[PDB]
Image (cartoon, helix red, strand yellow):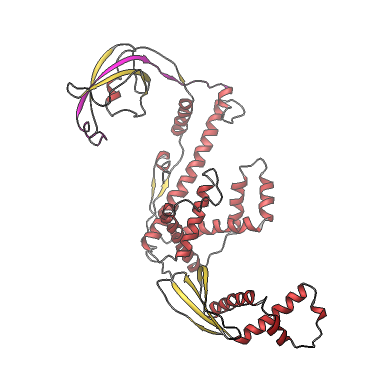
Amino acid sequence: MQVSVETTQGLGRRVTITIAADSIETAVKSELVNVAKKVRIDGFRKGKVPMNIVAQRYGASVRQDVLGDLMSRNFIDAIIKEKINPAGAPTYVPGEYKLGEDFTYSVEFEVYPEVELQGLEAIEVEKPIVEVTDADVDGMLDTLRKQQATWKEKDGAVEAEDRVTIDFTGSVDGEEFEGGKASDFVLAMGQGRMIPGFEDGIKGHKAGEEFTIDVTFPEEYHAENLKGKAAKFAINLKKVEERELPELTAEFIKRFGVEDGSVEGLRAEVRKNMERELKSAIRNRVKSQAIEGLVKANDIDVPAALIDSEIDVLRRQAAQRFGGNEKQALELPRELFEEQAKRRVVVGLLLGEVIRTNELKADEERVKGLIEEMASAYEDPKEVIEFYSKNKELMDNMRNVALEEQAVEAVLAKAKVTEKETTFNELMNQQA
């Protein structure tokens, strides 16, 4: 086989190959005899006519599949001896075929890119020293009770968090504006649903009195004819409620999955859950930092085929949530994932060069542990493990998950890892 290579653009390449007329004729002959064996007719052959002539007389129905099998077999040899490593699926491109003659074709593709891991020691990773304190647990419970609370009522103390019903009108300086039309409106203060300052003035009035308050619009208010300007409000206070942290009985505390309605048990529920949250936040804070460092210091050429497939993967994961619409995901506009797609492909090629350099292997003891954490959430962990173990498909993936954590640590190692104390809330900032 005669094989020439060509560099096209960036990672692009074009391998050209030429199969010999006779290599084709031989493959025809073979495919003919196989089809015959598979159909159980090989035995009726008598040799009256040699195999190189039946091929020349009955090879027709076999040609195309043959030529296609040859283009593939030959292309994989070629990139195995030239050591070429295509990224994504190649693209065959045949020239024309002249019956009985040689055949040349091309295969276009992009190769993985060479990676020179830089700045590893320049990357800085801040490791938070946190803990869930009694102060926290207390807060959370307070939140729970507030979540499912009851709107009681009082009279004469519009506190900072009460709910109130009102009628209002706004006067810029002696004029009512486009809005300010309030007919028995309900406002649960403390949530900043109103202009800042607005509800801070109503924090005194009695459950029934009327009064006027001064307020200013933020400078970037959408109403260009109100932003910045000062106004006054005619507030009609006719109701004043007070969220009353309800139930704390078994019917409540065990509603949170705490079998024995013991308050000492709701705390350990909340406690244990918060600590589980924290554990995850930390792993994210550390991991995201390391990875940002890695990506920022190593800009590399990303092959297109790879990016495409990650978009598809991202679109299918999007459909699956979008009520699931198999192959309606191929429909979601490309540029909606393009960016983060190219980002996964990059983090992968980089954490990959990290794996190569350090010749890392999926640590099976870790893989087992991952499988346990995972199984830990079901009624019977043992059966999930017995199931997972026998299925080499879910296993290799769980190896890749372990391998990836390992590739991270091998960056966290060679890196300026500072370290500081901080709150639970600081780490509860898993916004992105």
Residue 356, relative to residue 155: is it above or below? below
Q: Is residue 297 left or right of residue 59?
A: left
Magenta-colored stretch includes residue 238: yes
What range is drawn magenta here?
220-249
Question: Is residue 233 positioned above or below 131 on the image?
Answer: above
Q: Report x, y in % for residue 6.
A: 44, 79
Is 405 above or below relative to 224?
below
Does the image show residue 113?
A: yes
Q: Answer with the quarter of the image where residue 199 lies.
A: top left
Residue 219, image x and y in percent? 22, 35
Determine the residue positioned at 42% across, 62% down.
414
| Residue in the foreground of this view, choosing between 150 and 64 | 64
Does residue 366 appear to the left or right of 142 in the view shown? right
Q: Please state which of residues 331 and 263 is positioned toward the viewer in this rendering.
A: 331
For the image, the number of numbered tags is 0
Q: In this rendering, is residue 213 above or below 228?
A: above
Q: Is residue 420 left or right of residue 94?
A: left
Q: Residue at x 36, y 26 (%)?
A: 190
- The residue furthest left is 173
Residue 240 image position (x, y, % from top left) = 37, 16
Q: Residue 366 in the image: x percent, y percent?
A: 58, 55
